[PDB]
Image (cartoon, rainbow over the protein chains, first blue to last red):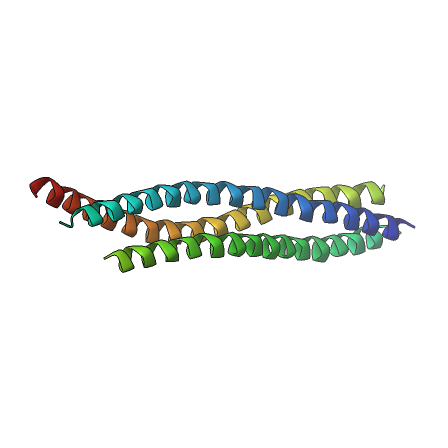
Length: 59
Length: 54
Length: 61
Protein backbone atom coordinates (compact mmCIF):
# COMPACT_ATOMS: atom_id res chain seq x y z
CA UNK A 1 0.00 0.00 0.00
CA UNK A 2 2.53 2.63 1.19
CA UNK A 3 5.38 1.65 -1.15
CA UNK A 4 3.08 1.89 -4.25
CA UNK A 5 1.57 5.24 -3.07
CA UNK A 6 5.00 6.88 -2.51
CA UNK A 7 6.37 5.55 -5.76
CA UNK A 8 3.36 6.85 -7.73
CA UNK A 9 3.60 10.28 -5.98
CA UNK A 10 7.31 10.27 -7.06
CA UNK A 11 6.35 9.38 -10.68
CA UNK A 12 3.74 12.23 -11.04
CA UNK A 13 5.86 14.91 -9.29
CA UNK A 14 8.98 13.97 -11.07
CA UNK A 15 7.12 14.06 -14.38
CA UNK A 16 5.92 17.62 -13.61
CA UNK A 17 9.43 18.59 -12.57
CA UNK A 18 10.95 17.40 -15.88
CA UNK A 19 8.45 19.64 -17.73
CA UNK A 20 9.14 22.71 -15.60
CA UNK A 21 12.89 22.41 -16.06
CA UNK A 22 12.77 22.18 -19.81
CA UNK A 23 10.04 24.87 -19.98
CA UNK A 24 12.28 27.33 -17.94
CA UNK A 25 15.51 26.37 -19.72
CA UNK A 26 14.05 26.66 -23.15
CA UNK A 27 12.62 30.16 -22.22
CA UNK A 28 16.22 31.22 -21.16
CA UNK A 29 17.42 29.90 -24.51
CA UNK A 30 14.81 31.99 -26.37
CA UNK A 31 16.01 34.97 -24.34
CA UNK A 32 19.68 34.50 -25.43
CA UNK A 33 18.79 33.79 -29.09
CA UNK A 34 16.85 37.05 -29.16
CA UNK A 35 19.96 38.91 -27.97
CA UNK A 36 22.09 37.28 -30.72
CA UNK A 37 19.35 37.86 -33.32
CA UNK A 38 19.35 41.60 -32.50
CA UNK A 39 23.10 41.50 -32.95
CA UNK A 40 22.94 39.70 -36.31
CA UNK A 41 20.21 42.21 -37.55
CA UNK A 42 22.64 45.05 -36.79
CA UNK A 43 25.59 43.32 -38.49
CA UNK A 44 23.48 42.66 -41.58
CA UNK A 45 22.50 46.37 -41.77
CA UNK A 46 26.26 47.32 -41.45
CA UNK A 47 27.14 44.92 -44.29
CA UNK A 48 24.37 46.52 -46.44
CA UNK A 49 26.10 49.82 -45.75
CA UNK A 50 29.51 48.57 -46.91
CA UNK A 51 27.92 47.08 -50.03
CA UNK A 52 26.60 50.44 -51.18
CA UNK A 53 29.74 52.17 -50.05
CA UNK A 54 31.84 49.73 -52.12
CA UNK A 55 29.76 50.26 -55.27
CA UNK A 56 30.02 54.02 -54.67
CA UNK A 57 33.79 53.75 -54.48
CA UNK A 58 33.54 53.05 -58.25
CA UNK A 59 34.28 55.57 -59.91
CA UNK B 1 6.83 -1.83 7.99
CA UNK B 2 8.16 0.86 8.00
CA UNK B 3 11.81 1.93 8.00
CA UNK B 4 12.36 -0.75 5.36
CA UNK B 5 9.46 0.90 3.35
CA UNK B 6 10.82 4.46 3.81
CA UNK B 7 14.25 3.30 2.65
CA UNK B 8 12.92 1.49 -0.48
CA UNK B 9 10.78 4.47 -1.40
CA UNK B 10 13.66 6.90 -1.08
CA UNK B 11 15.87 4.70 -3.25
CA UNK B 12 13.12 4.79 -5.85
CA UNK B 13 13.01 8.64 -5.53
CA UNK B 14 16.75 8.88 -5.96
CA UNK B 15 17.07 6.87 -9.20
CA UNK B 16 13.86 8.39 -10.64
CA UNK B 17 14.76 12.00 -9.83
CA UNK B 18 18.34 11.71 -11.06
CA UNK B 19 17.19 10.22 -14.36
CA UNK B 20 14.84 13.09 -14.72
CA UNK B 21 17.59 15.68 -14.02
CA UNK B 22 19.57 14.00 -16.84
CA UNK B 23 16.44 13.83 -19.12
CA UNK B 24 15.66 17.55 -18.61
CA UNK B 25 19.26 18.60 -19.24
CA UNK B 26 19.41 16.41 -22.52
CA UNK B 27 16.13 17.87 -23.98
CA UNK B 28 17.00 21.42 -23.08
CA UNK B 29 20.56 21.01 -24.54
CA UNK B 30 18.93 19.61 -27.67
CA UNK B 31 16.51 22.55 -28.01
CA UNK B 32 19.52 24.92 -27.51
CA UNK B 33 21.58 23.06 -30.31
CA UNK B 34 18.54 23.54 -32.54
CA UNK B 35 18.48 27.35 -31.99
CA UNK B 36 22.30 27.40 -32.35
CA UNK B 37 22.21 25.83 -35.83
CA UNK B 38 19.92 28.62 -37.07
CA UNK B 39 22.06 31.41 -35.50
CA UNK B 40 25.38 29.98 -36.75
CA UNK B 41 23.92 29.42 -40.26
CA UNK B 42 22.83 33.05 -40.36
CA UNK B 43 26.32 34.18 -39.38
CA UNK B 44 27.91 31.76 -41.87
CA UNK B 45 25.90 33.49 -44.58
CA UNK B 46 26.85 36.94 -43.55
CA UNK B 47 30.59 36.20 -43.55
CA UNK B 48 30.16 34.52 -46.95
CA UNK B 49 28.50 37.72 -48.37
CA UNK B 50 31.29 39.93 -46.85
CA UNK B 51 33.95 37.65 -48.42
CA UNK B 52 32.21 37.62 -51.82
CA UNK B 53 31.75 41.44 -51.58
CA UNK B 54 35.49 41.84 -50.87
CA UNK C 1 3.79 8.36 9.07
CA UNK C 2 6.18 6.60 6.69
CA UNK C 3 4.21 7.90 3.67
CA UNK C 4 4.40 11.51 4.87
CA UNK C 5 8.19 11.13 5.37
CA UNK C 6 8.70 9.41 1.98
CA UNK C 7 6.68 12.12 0.17
CA UNK C 8 8.54 14.98 1.95
CA UNK C 9 11.85 13.41 0.89
CA UNK C 10 10.46 13.19 -2.66
CA UNK C 11 9.45 16.94 -2.60
CA UNK C 12 12.91 18.17 -1.46
CA UNK C 13 14.68 15.85 -3.91
CA UNK C 14 12.51 16.93 -6.92
CA UNK C 15 12.77 20.67 -6.04
CA UNK C 16 16.59 20.40 -5.88
CA UNK C 17 16.45 18.53 -9.22
CA UNK C 18 14.45 21.23 -11.04
CA UNK C 19 16.94 23.89 -9.81
CA UNK C 20 19.95 21.76 -10.86
CA UNK C 21 18.61 20.93 -14.33
CA UNK C 22 17.73 24.57 -15.08
CA UNK C 23 21.16 25.72 -13.83
CA UNK C 24 23.05 23.17 -15.92
CA UNK C 25 20.92 23.69 -19.09
CA UNK C 26 21.34 27.39 -18.77
CA UNK C 27 25.23 27.02 -18.29
CA UNK C 28 25.22 25.00 -21.48
CA UNK C 29 23.18 27.65 -23.44
CA UNK C 30 25.62 30.24 -21.98
CA UNK C 31 28.70 28.44 -23.34
CA UNK C 32 27.17 27.94 -26.81
CA UNK C 33 25.99 31.58 -26.95
CA UNK C 34 29.45 32.85 -25.73
CA UNK C 35 31.17 31.00 -28.65
CA UNK C 36 28.90 32.63 -31.22
CA UNK C 37 29.24 36.05 -29.53
CA UNK C 38 32.97 35.66 -29.92
CA UNK C 39 32.66 34.84 -33.64
CA UNK C 40 30.24 37.76 -34.05
CA UNK C 41 32.58 40.18 -32.23
CA UNK C 42 35.36 39.49 -34.74
CA UNK C 43 33.13 40.22 -37.68
CA UNK C 44 31.67 43.37 -36.17
CA UNK C 45 35.22 44.68 -35.80
CA UNK C 46 36.15 43.83 -39.44
CA UNK C 47 33.02 45.50 -40.75
CA UNK C 48 33.55 48.72 -38.76
CA UNK C 49 37.10 48.79 -40.13
CA UNK C 50 36.01 48.18 -43.77
CA UNK C 51 33.22 50.74 -43.44
CA UNK C 52 35.52 53.50 -42.18
CA UNK C 53 38.19 52.98 -44.82
CA UNK C 54 35.62 52.88 -47.64
CA UNK C 55 33.76 55.83 -46.09
CA UNK C 56 37.19 57.54 -45.98
CA UNK C 57 38.08 56.67 -49.62
CA UNK C 58 34.68 58.10 -50.78
CA UNK C 59 35.29 61.42 -48.97
CA UNK C 60 38.83 61.74 -50.28
CA UNK C 61 37.70 60.95 -53.86
